[PDB]
Every structure is written in structure tokens, then in C-alpha cells.
Length: 325
Ligand SMILES: [Fe+3]
Image 1 (tube, rainbow, N blue to C red):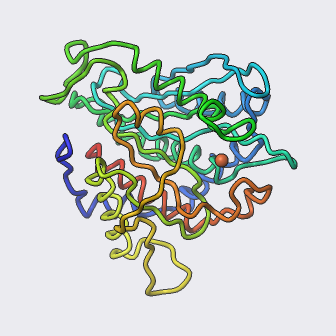
Image 2 (image 1 turned 90 degrees about the horizontal axis):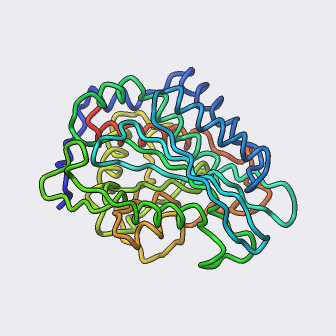
């Protein structure tokens, strides 16, 4: 059983999280435009993207940390900088939403990585912005739960994906947090039977978004441990559809992104170094990958906007339910 009682979103809140005004659309797209540039490790546009993320979240009065370091790669020594934003640093437990902000250095030409992961980056910032008032209110409760957003650097391989060439930022951060010791007594309102020995134990669940923005994604539950959390995403999507709040190409259709079916697939991503340290993971990545995956066609025009809108409604409702906004 999940360590936190997961109370179903009231209808009033579901309906609110499920509407998207044209200024909602406009705000998200304006956010997204900042990420639809090549973001290769070490580059100027990469530092500009990080600066944008940092300022956006500092403007919202979040605590923002830049976890920077240099690491050896097949292309020589490289600088990396993870961005960690925490709404209430004192709160013992974090609901962590994450993605990567670097883009693949593509051998053929300029690679935008619109789904991989410009859309997930923008979705995290859009969540922070659009739920800001509710989040600021939730932070005052002293209930020991907060929201945390991690934008990992160096997710992509420089050459052939391997244990040593991939996940530079997440490998670094998981180790950093594992070795940084702390205890429940130093923290605000930890749950009763919490075993807190280090920073990594404060990660209540890590929801990792990746390869989003293409039409008709298929998600599955990748971890039995987080099946209670995963099923809330299934339930929210079902309720949005029942209420007629999803955008579909024709009348009398339903989205079915979050399957209840079992899968036996394994995908390496930024969750791995945390998974190895007992952090519960929900991996929101489609299977199969978008047809555009790691091609020069993973670009702005190939994004499917109605799907992005539907996903934003699900994620907003999810956060709202988890934090009881
Ligand atoms: Fe990729």
C-alpha cells in the first residue's frame, strides 16, 4: 500500500484542471518556443535554456539549485548542470516531476528534439505557472509534502549509448543525494514510519516525462511498486473523457493513453540511477517511441497539439490530486 492516502479529486477540481482557455494554450506555446532550439551540452543555446528555466522558477518564488559539474565523455571533458526547483525545501517529502533538457548531438545535422524532451520541459514549467496560486497556498499547510522539478542535463549519449556514455546528470545527482545524509528530525513533518537517512529518501515518487508531444502515445505501468500512483493517472484520464474534456478528432471517441495492460518492456532513462537507490518511479514515456525518435524530423511541426493539451490536463489534475490543491 502507498505510504500516502490518495484522496480522489473532487469533480469541481477535475472540471477546473480539465479546461484549457486560449490564453492557457497561448501561455504553454510561448513557454514551449523557448525550448524549440538545439540544446547540445556545453553550447550557448543550452546555457540560455537553463537560464530561462532558472529565471522562470525563481520568478515563481521556488528555491532553485544548479547542480553543476564536469564529466569525462567520449568527446572529452564536458560541463553539465542539472536544475532542481523545489517549492518548499523544508517539506520532508517531495513529489518529483522530471525530464531532461539537453538535446542529442545528431551526426546528420541540427536536432531540435521537440518531443525529446522540449515538450516535457515546457510541460513542467507550464505546470508550475498555471498552478502557481494553488501551489503557493499548499506550501503554507505544513503538511510535509511539496512539489519538486528536476531538469536533468546530459541524458543523451555522445556516441553509442552505454553505462558510461548516457545519463550523466542523473547518475551524478542520484549519487550526490544518496551521500548527503539527513534525518526526519531535521525536516518538516515526515510521515510516521518514514525511514529517512539521506536526500534520496525524501523523493516520495519520481514521475519522469520523456518523448511526449507526438500523437496517440501508449503508456503502461512499468513498476508494480507505483501501480497505486499510475492508476490515478488512468482514473483521471477516464474522468476527463467521461466529462467530454479531451480533444479528439471526431465526436464519441475517448483517449486511451494510460493503458491498464501489463507490459514487459525495459527502457533506460534518467530514472535508472534513482530506481537503483529504491526511489519509486512512474515512467511516462510512450511505447513504441514516436516514429520521429532521434531523426531530424523530431521537430516543431510534427508535434501534435491536441495530444499535448490532453496530456497537460491529465498532468495538472494529477498534481492537483496528489498535493490536494
Ligand atoms: Fe533521446
